[PDB]
Length: 464
Ligand code: HEM
Image (tube, rainbow, N blue to C red; front, side):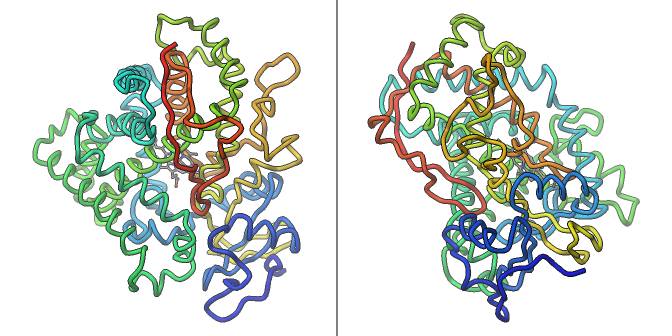
């Protein structure tokens, strides 16, 4: 009949004094040790119910999916989105935009041979670019993001960016900068005090300029499409949305208008780029750290695929080890540690607790990815967490990097195809040489807040 228990908050600052903005995950897990897997925390004035561990998260987001299907907030992103767009919208707006987005993504090849061919082709471009380095030590950050970003870019903008495109690099920097900021102490402090901070000088202002930069770019691309639009022959996601907008012009209450187009497109562009990119980057670092794992991956690739042909998505079924490795990378990486906030759609009764309608919820995906009840050694990187005795792939109900439930990631299909084809093709063609000794490679995160960011590093890609 009452909300989950938790530390007594103070007016306005909430539980700020009982938290550490540089390590929110750790702070909440600590409080969790005292109040239990389901507790209440006050992030500044924001009252939030925190769900820790697999059971609590699944019970809420899956067993009571409709009740927890609301979209919470992320102050930094809300600065530009203001509740528009598929990701941060709620109610009728979210229902229309999500349905349309999923359909439009599929119409443009997502989950089909079309997008697979697009990915294989861009993968071929990654290979060329890596060979272009001549085995020199480099920062793989943008090599990876350019390739990844061109996949979702092909869908939303009609086609790919040239790797030499300076505005392209510029946009990628904006995305990287935003994910970093939201994962820093100030970024997490902003989640608590955005009401005042959005108006104060500080790092947040610089972050805002990056978002503004992305919005301007999108608004620009949309204008260009508008003035070259063939109502019966859409080239991309944008044209599709524009056509829908024309069809809905006479509906006072349609959700299909310019702001939702711009924001939805911006969200998919960022969503489809930085998440996959960060994962690839963390993955290669993890493989250099564990030579024994790269060795096995090479054995499976050579046997199953060989050295001549391009790997294809169907090869995954014949490659249990690679599938286990990518899973372990996503589990260890814990890219979106606290997921994207949800909120109860209406008054809810959850585990003998009462959550009034509108209550914000923090599904601690990281605590699920490292639930000691589902993984033998959660803190270690070990592909075995995903293999049975005969070395066959073993799924886990605790594997939730894309979250679960009604507002789960609908980019998962695309993401998985990308992770498999990029990782495999790169490993088929190169062995990884780290700038330092494996024993010395630090795989602990550089930042953890909204996202998990790996430490900066360099490496070389040596031909096989
Ligand atoms: C390895 C890559 C990715 C990870 C780890 C990931 C993770 C997430 C997570 C944790 C959520 C929130 C789920 C929830 O609220 O329950 C989410 C939502 C979302 N993701 Fe992803 N994602 C990835 C890639 C993608 C890609 C490639 C796209 C783009 C096609 C994308 C599109 C979205 C969208 C549009 C949402 C919002 C859905 C809604 O509000 O209904 N994601 N993602």
